[PDB]
Length: 358
Ligand SMILES: Cc1onc(-c2ccccc2Cl)c1C(=O)NCC(=O)O
Image 1 (cartoon, protein in one colour):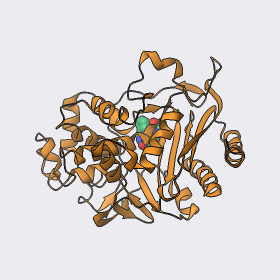
Image 2 (image 1 turned 180 degrees about the vertical axis):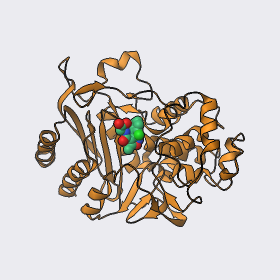
Image 3 (image 1 turned 120 degrees about the vertical axis):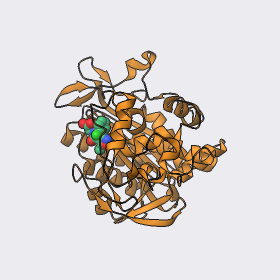
C-alpha cells in the first residue's frame, strides 16, 4: 500500500485492537476506487488460525444493506413497490393494525414499533404469522423510527415473494453472483468452513444462532475482499452492468426519513458530508437497547446524494462490523472483527482514517 494509507490505517487500528482486546480484525480501505487490505490477529484462537483476506466474518446488521439492495432490485424489476400495503404480499395478515403499513415502513423501521427482535419462541411459519397478527403498534405508521430486525426482516421476506425464489436464492442470483461476491454466504458451505472465524463473547467462541428472519436481518457472512467489492459497488453503481441491480443500489441510498442529522435508506443510513464526526460517532452508540425517535418524511425521497457519509454498523454476539463510504470522494472503509466492541470506537476509527485520506 501507499505509505500514507499504511500509516493512517496502522496508527488507528493497532491501538483500537489493544484497547478493545479484539482477537482478529480485517480492514479494507477503498482509495480512489482501489482496495487496500490489512489483517491482524486470529480467526480461531484455539487452533491458531490467523485472519486472512479469505477469512469469513459474521456481518450482523450490515446484512441489512444486502437486504435493502435486494429489495431495491425487486422494485427496479417491477416485482414490488414500496408504496404497496404489506397485506398485498401477505394476505393472511388480516389484523386491522396492518391497514396503512406499507413495504416502505417495514424497510425503514417506521411501521409503528415493531420490536428489535423476533421472539426466540417464534420458530415455525405459523408462529411468525401469529406474531405479526398479534403485534400492537405503539404509533401510527410513518411517525417514529425504531430500529428492528422484525421490520426489515419481514420486508426482505416479502420482497422476494413475487419472484418465487427463496430469500437466499434471490440474494445469490440477483446480488452476490452479479457482483462477483463469491465468498459471501447466508449459509456457510462445508467447503468454506476452514475460513469461518469464530466470534468471541466473554472469551467464548461463538457463532450466530438460527432464528426467524435471520437471513434477512443479520445472516450474511463475508470476507474482507468481498466486502471491499460491496463497497466499490455501492460507491459506483453505474459501473454495474445489471440494470435492475444498478437501480436497486441507488434506491437503497435514497433518503426516505430524517431523524436529527441522519437519513434512513434501505439498510444504509446516511448523513450529509462533511459530517460532524461527533454526530456520527455518538449517533452510532446503540443508545441503548431501544431508541424510539420521531421521523420526518422526505416527500418524495431524495435520490442518492453523492456528498454523503453512507454507513452501517453490524453486530452478532461474537462479531462487530462497520462499513462507511463517501461517494463524492470515491473513498470507503470496511472493518470486520470477531468481537462485538462498542460502535463509537468503530465510527471514531473509521472517521480518523477516512478524514486523513480525504
Ligand atoms: C444491533 C443489532 O441488530 N441486530 C442484532 C442482532 C444480531 C444477531 C442476533 C440478534 C440480534 Cl438482536 C443486533 C445486536 O446487538 N446483536 C448482538 C447479539 O446478538 O448479541
